[PDB]
Amino acid sequence: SQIVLPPHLERIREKLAENIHELWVMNKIELGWQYGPVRDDNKRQHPCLVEFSKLPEQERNYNLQMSLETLKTLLALGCHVGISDEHAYQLTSGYKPAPMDLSFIKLTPSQEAMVDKLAENAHNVWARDRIRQRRNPRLVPYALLDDRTKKSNKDSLREAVRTLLGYGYNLEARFRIFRAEKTYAVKAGRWYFEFEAVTAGDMRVGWSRPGCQPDQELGSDERAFAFDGFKAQRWHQGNEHYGRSWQAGDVVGCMVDMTEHTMMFTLNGEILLDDSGSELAFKDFDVGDGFIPVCS
Image (cartoon, rainbow, N blue to C red; front, side, top):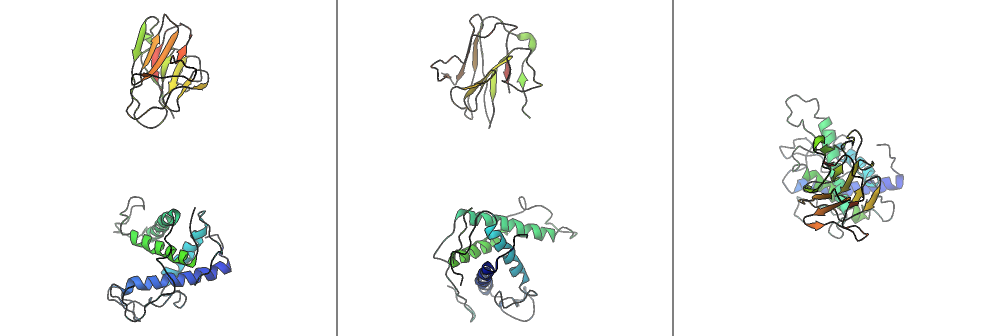
């Protein structure tokens, strides 16, 4: 609302709203609803078949006050179009309106995408008009109510944009930590366990001292020795790139020598590799109070 319309753009928008109202006549003159003085939309009587500027805001106000906010919205969503151009077949009953063309230029992505916001806006102000009235089955929002009868108002806005580009105005726009028991802290031998990464994001798998804190989060300490399956980097008091990303349906796995001070992480049998030409993910650790499997 608080984007003021320039007057040279106001004459543009009034000509284009005239050439949108000829479509608003033409989609009602095909189905067999004629002009009259009385307002009987179910009985084919419709006094809004006179064009946009010539009808007042007592009959065609639903198409004029819609067009003002829609054209305010035409250069408000980043899809800016200023003054770069000039604003200016079925059988009918006698009035076949043709101010301009429609099948010369088809439109871009953010016009048919902004038509969705226009349909949401119209549905939301209509639902605002449907808030209080009881026995209304329209008491659910735009993103869940049936969106197929709203596609005609998407077609009207998209053909309004077709008229716009005929006139020459285009549109182009926390983390939980998991571990096994403290008493199984292995201090000798050659051990391995496996892990599957399924859905999107941080999978931080490793071996930790039992004195690790799940109070904080992982990797930025000396107790944890881990690798992020996401972003292909390792984690113990810092970062360095290592290996590849995880895949949806991987089996990562982790192996630890304890008599030797080494630790190597795999992926589906492929031993994951560092850019130093060594597949051993962590080396030369302290053989302290043992190490337990941990995943974040």
